[PDB]
Length: 272
Ligand SMILES: COCCNC(=N)NCCC[C@H](N)C(=O)O
Image (cartoon, rainbow, N blue to C red; front, side):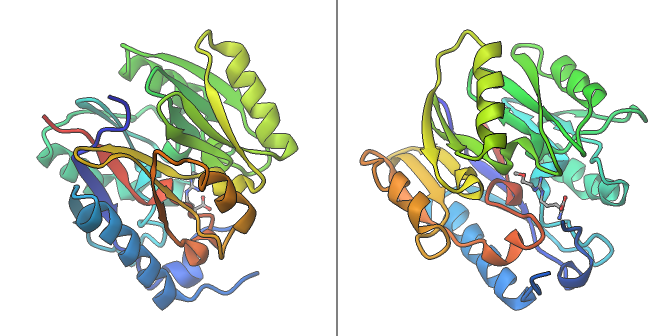
């Protein structure tokens, strides 16, 4: 059953995020970001019933909230990544310990010529696509392939300071939410060309709004966290058509200013 999760790892955001998190002018309202982040944690843990592991903020790591970039979990195995920005590399320490306590088999990306950000990795339920980007390189992608041996891994070039999931993510079984920009469409075609699996797509006019979270929840069924109609009205009208999903609008406007989207803020785990 694709999208099953029992546990999520998240991490509180530091005061330092407002001035120190990496970003490609928009002033960050750190109190509003904390509010948005608390609301997102509420959905995962309270509303959907996942067991959430809330990591404490570390003021020395302005981007620590973005736990997705530091770990990729597939089944009973966790790849601890080697993030592409060297300043984010100590974020792995706390995540390794949390994933240890969750009884995952841990593989650490230690190779000094390898980098990977978890935000470059799209797992479809059938295979992985891995963005080759400013943050993820070919070697990082190879070590992901070596770690998740049961699954095919293919790479796709990603331009211009983007991550693969800057413009896509899974919206359901067999369903890739994908943005309409020249970048996103060029990337989708490459992915579709490299795989024999025939995916369906859900095309949205705002690349950013293609980053959503799908879960398959006991006694709830298909569930999708997506950006709000106040943030991306024309994309929310597209998700509204998913009549068999429980749709949950989640705001992420403040963390978006330092390139933080929905998937970025949690690592999801399915535990026996
Ligand atoms: C889904 O990935 C979207 C892109 N964002 C991402 N991977 N991580 C969050 C932002 C991390 C950091 N602030 C940066 O600019 O690198």
